[PDB]
Image (tube, coloured by chain):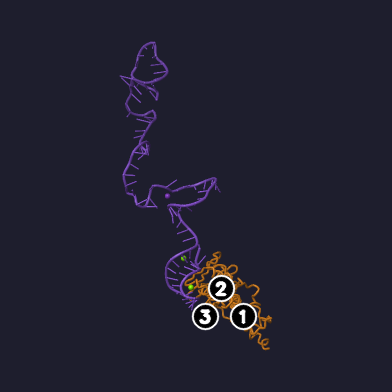
Chain colours: A orange, B purple
RNA sequence: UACCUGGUUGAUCCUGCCAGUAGUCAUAUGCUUGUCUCAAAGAUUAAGCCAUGCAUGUGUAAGUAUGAACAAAUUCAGACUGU
């Protein structure tokens, strides 16, 4: 079946780690997609966003390969992006799905004004940049919906954000850079220091230290 | 009610525009057009030129009646006193 090759994979298969937030807290790299499948696999959905052909010139013509862009998300604060290039479309799509699973990140959602109910928009103004494409997200009031193009709109929908205002500059017709800028903007949500985070951090044992004895075998 | 997509390349990321998409109590034209309620309409070019018809008249007890105007009365007198 699955034979983990990493300490994190062993812990996830042994049920020692039960939530993706435990891994996110210590910023540990995730190198096996079975970890994500076990943790949040049931609620994850995938979608192929674009199949892009690329060509390399050779002495005997053009060698064509296909680029697959895949977005995964649970619609509840987790989203991932995957890009893979392969000779066959199916292989590229499979690799892109694996990479999108491996890159899932937590998305912070906040309130525009009054803080009643679940969060509905981005906590603050965030901006992402890939290549020349820059994507800006602005908090929006409840009921405003997702005001974004179809690619950013899909990325935001997979992240579970209910309403947001967006603006884009640059070559947004470069779909890869557009989606990557949106992904970077979403990732930057948890890096902004707000007054609610001013409390002193109270550290907890890392999984590799907490379960060192188990991993010692 | 804070949104983009096609097009320069063997392929790439750009600048940049062309094209698309939507709107006008916005004009015109094409095809089509069964019912109800609303409703613009010779401004744009020529404040260019105009046949014909109409679009400014007017009376109360209370300015001026002798129509040779109509009506009712008067057998005798009457300035006039109805229209
Ligand atoms: K009019
Ligand atoms: Mg604008
Ligand atoms: Mg070509």
The chain ID associated with circle 2 is: A
Label 1 with label 2: CB-CB less than 8 Å: no
Say which label, 3 or 1, has the lower sequence index: 1
Residue corresponding to mark 2? A51
Residue corresponding to mark 1? A23
Toward the viewer: A114 or A86?
A: A86
Q: Position of residue A64 (x, y in %)?
A: 54, 77
Furthest residue toward bottom: A216
From mark 3 to mark 1, how far is it between C-alphas? 49 Å
Mark 2 vs mark 3, foreground winner is 3
Position of residue B30 relative to residue A98, above or below, is: above
Structural crowding at the residue carrying mark 3, measured as other residues with C-alpha within 10 Å and reported as few (<14), some (14–19) or many (≥20): few
Q: Position of residue B67 (x, y in %)?
A: 34, 21
Q: Quadrant of the C terminus of chain A?
A: bottom right
Say which label, 1 or 2, has the lower sequence index: 1
The chain ID associated with circle 1 is: A
Q: Which mark is residue A126?
A: none
Q: Residue at x 60, y 69 (%)?
A: A118
Q: Position of residue B52 (x, y in %)?
A: 35, 37
Structural crowding at the residue carrying mark 1, measured as other residues with C-alpha within 10 Å and reported as few (<14), some (14–19) or many (≥20): some
Q: Which mark is residue A60?
A: 3
SS state under label 1: helix
- The answer, for residue A18, to whether it is visible in the render is yes
The chain ID associated with circle 3 is: A
From mark 1 to mark 2, how far is it between C-alphas? 32 Å
Same chain shared by disc 1 and disc 2: yes
Q: How many marks?
A: 3
Q: Residue at x 57, y 68 (%)?
A: A162
Toward the viewer: A117 or A50?
A: A50
């Amino acid at each position: 079946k699955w034979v983990p090759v990493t300490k994190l994979g062993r812990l996830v298969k042994d049920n020692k780690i039960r939530s993706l937030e435990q891994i996110y807290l210590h910023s540990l790299p995730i190198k096996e997609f079975q970890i994500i499948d076990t943790l949040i696999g049931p609620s994850l959905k995938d979608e192929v966003m674009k199949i892009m052909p690329v060509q390399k010139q050779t002495r005997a013509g053009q060698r064509t390969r296909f680029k697959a862009f895949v977005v995964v998300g649970d619609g509840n604060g987790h989203v991932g992006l995957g890009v893979k290039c392969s000779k066959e479309v199916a292989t590229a799509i499979r690799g892109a799905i694996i990479l999108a699973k491996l890159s899932v990140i937590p998305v912070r959602r906040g309130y525009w004004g009054n803080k009643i109910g679940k969060p509905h928009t981005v906590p603050c103004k965030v901006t992402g940049k890939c290549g020349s494409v820059t994507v800006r997200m602005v908090p929006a009031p409840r009921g405003a919906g997702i005001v974004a193009a179809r690619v950013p709109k899909k990325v935001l929908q997979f992240a579970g954000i209910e309403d947001v205002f967006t603006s884009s500059r640059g070559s947004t017709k470069t779909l890869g850079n557009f989606v990557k800028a949106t992904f970077d903007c979403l990732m930057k949500t948890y890096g902004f220091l707000t007054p609610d985070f001013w409390k002193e951090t109270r550290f907890t044992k890392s999984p590799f230290q907490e379960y060192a004895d188990i991993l010692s075998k």
